[PDB]
Image (tube, rainbow over all chains, first blue to last red; front, side):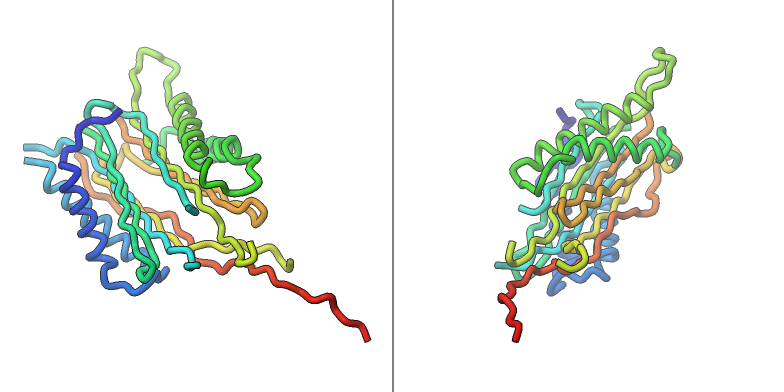
Amino acid sequence: AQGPSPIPTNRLKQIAADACNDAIGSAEFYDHAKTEQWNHQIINTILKAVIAESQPTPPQFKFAVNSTIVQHLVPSRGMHSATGAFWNDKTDGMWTYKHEGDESKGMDVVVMLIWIAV
Amino acid sequence: GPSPIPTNRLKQIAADACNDAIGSAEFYDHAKTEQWNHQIINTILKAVIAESQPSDSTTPPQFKFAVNSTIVQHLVPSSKDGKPHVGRRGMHSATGAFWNDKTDGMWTYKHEGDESKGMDVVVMLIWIAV
Amino acid sequence: LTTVPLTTIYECPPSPVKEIFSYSKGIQT
């Protein structure tokens, strides 16, 4: 079980979709030499936005953001990710998001947010 | 900062969980990956919780823990020998945090398959104090 | 109290698959 998200999930989905397209919206394909700056950008954007939009007073959450850029398989599945936790089921939680590329894009993004109260 | 558990112990906890889950798989099977990851996550959580726990039981849980596990299939040749070689898709995983820098932390493990195995496992562990 | 620290990694550059080829019988003459 999980605690209520400190930011509505629909807001999160758009903080996340926006951070992703900002970083990789103009990319033509997967380029491994750029993935580190791409993730650097994606994580910082999401983190800044959730810190900002979660607090009115002191900060009351710890946040962790994980981002994974994954190259598509060559066209004519192959990876599964999951998270378990031992936290406070009434205050703490996680949210995940897949930015799914089409065939021309050649890459997906997988984002996870974890929040820990106080 | 420093982990509640020595990284050398973490490493054999993580390696044991991975072989406990996929040690006898002949091949990657997308139908079983959920069970496999469940299993790996479960095993690592129980074990890091145990080895965290002070002998003085009058002490309440000192850490929160999250375990993320990923299983990735190797690239499959077009036909479905020379020297063994593993094809892999590209990927990059990073993590940022808004944390207590001195108490909270992360640790990662990779379980690289050989060519015959056909898949890799990556594990991230997060600990949040208090 | 709580701050924004440096970022960390897991990383894998793309690597080509080992293709398996089809061979003829081979002719000795």
